[PDB]
Image 1 (tube, rainbow, N blue to C red):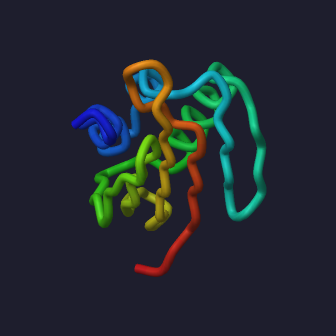
Image 2: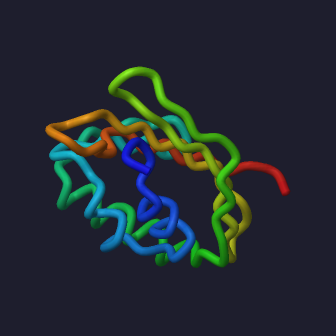
Image 3: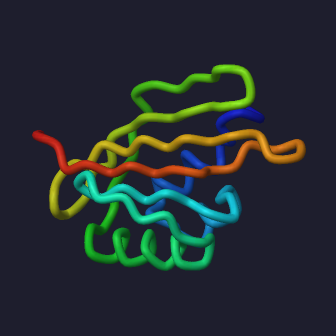
Length: 110
């Protein structure tokens, strides 16, 4: 739906940085193992492309989705060749669409 576009979920299922880029805000706070780097859309897309190449994705399960006013989130588990990662995406309404402004990715147990 509007708050969590199906395409965001499909992008993660496919390990597609190019699909994901469609839903990114002008700046995205990427958090890998707790280190935050707030970068522009192009650099965020490149960082996700590297992440998806290093850790080849076989699937993505959505665990939770939600909304609070003009903010939304989706939390899921990404299965990869190097194990599972929890993905936490935070979106906010910009004009008439919800765009990703933070992606936190943490390596988790199987």
